[PDB]
Image (cartoon, coloured by chain):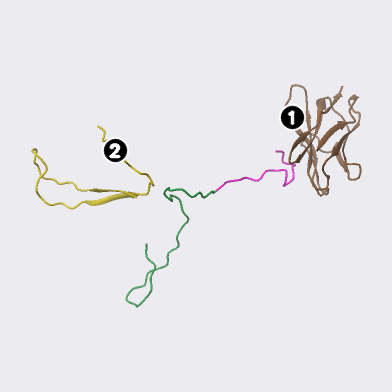
Chain colours: A green, B brown, C yellow
């Protein structure tokens, strides 16, 4: 891997975020965006569960 | 099926020139990328020159820029390497490389610059 | 899921466990998917 190599010759850095199906705890997830709360109004909500 | 053989080697002095060839079969050169590698005695194998599959862009190693020239022939299915302004550090056995399914490495031809 | 409840019971009785009332509050929960048959405590 020389700096004068082409873009197919110079490497592509790889990580693998594999998801398998086993009876294991889901430990790492993506973020959950949460809005601001409103009070004293007839409103739908999405709480933590 | 796929076989590479190298020819065009010889003995040259400092400042000479040579033209190596790598005859190819079992694959088209316009659909695959090729590389040239060399093996100095007592040193590891290092990349020399390469042509991409489209044939537009050719690349050379950092020690051999400005002096080497790699070329291909579509009809004869032979991969060439024109080498100029030769130093005695280029004493090596030259191999042509391709990745068609598996990797195929030729027998190589001894080129000594002295 | 495997879960553990606990309580502290600060009274003193060296004979046996007392006859009072104490409800146990949970600590953790963990999915394991493991068919546990037996266990062994250690010192």
Q: How many callouts does the rendering have?
A: 2
The stretch drawn in magenta includes residue A2 = yes
State the residue in front, B37 or A18: A18
At horizontal 61% and vertical 45% (from top left) the residue drawn is A14
Q: Position of residue B31 (x, y in %)?
A: 80, 48
Q: Which mark is residue B45?
A: 1
For the residues labelled 2 and 1, the Cα–Cα distance comes to 58 Å
Q: Give the mark toward the camera: 2 or 1.
A: 2
State the residue in front, C40 or A11: C40
Secondary structure category for the residue under label 1? strand
The reply to the same-chain question for discs 2 and 1 is no
Q: Quadrant of residue B23?
A: top right
> Are circles 2 and 1 on residues that touch, CB within 8 Å?
no
Label 2, on which residue? C39
Q: Position of residue C19 (x, y in %)?
A: 9, 48
Q: Which mark is residue A5?
A: none
For the N terminus of chain B, give its image quadrant. top right
At horizontal 46% and vertical 57% (from top left) the residue drawn is A31
Going by the image, does B26 lie left or right of C28? right
At horizontal 78% and vertical 43% (from top left) the residue drawn is B33
For the C terminus of chain B, give its image quadrant. top right
Q: Chain of mark 1?
A: B
Q: Position of residue C4 (x, y in %)?
A: 27, 47
Q: What's the magenta bit mostly, secondary-structure-wise?
A: loop
- Neighbour class for label 2 at 10 Å: few (<14), some, many (≥20)? few
- Over which residues does the magenta segment extend? A1-16
Q: Position of residue B49 (x, y in %)?
A: 80, 38
Q: Quadrant of residue B77?
A: top right
């Amino acid at each position: 891997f020389q700096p004068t190599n082409g873009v197919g010759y110079q490497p592509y850095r790889v990580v693998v975020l594999s998801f398998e199906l086993l009876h294991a705890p889901a430990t790492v997830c993506g973020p959950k965006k949460s809005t601001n709360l409103v009070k004293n109004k007839c409103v739908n909500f999405n709480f933590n569960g | 099926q796929v076989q590479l053989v190298e020819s065009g080697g010889g003995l040259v002095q400092a400042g000479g020139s040579l033209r190596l060839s790598c005859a190819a079969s079992g694959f088209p050169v316009k659909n695959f990328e090729m590389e040239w590698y060399r093996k100095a005695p007592g040193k590891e194998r290092e990349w020399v020159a390469a042509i991409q599959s489209g044939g537009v862009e050719t690349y050379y190693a950092d020690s051999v820029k400005g002096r080497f020239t790699i070329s291909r022939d579509n009809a004869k299915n032979t991969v060439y390497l024109q080498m100029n302004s030769l130093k005695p550090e280029d004493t090596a056995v030259y191999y042509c490389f391709v990745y068609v399914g598996r990797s195929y490495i030729g027998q190589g031809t001894q080129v000594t610059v002295s | 899921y495997f879960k553990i409840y606990s309580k502290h019971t600060p009274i003193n009785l060296v004979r046996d466990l007392p006859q009072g009332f104490s409800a146990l509050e949970p600590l953790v929960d963990l999915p394991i998917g493991i068919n546990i048959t037996r266990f062994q405590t250690l010192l």
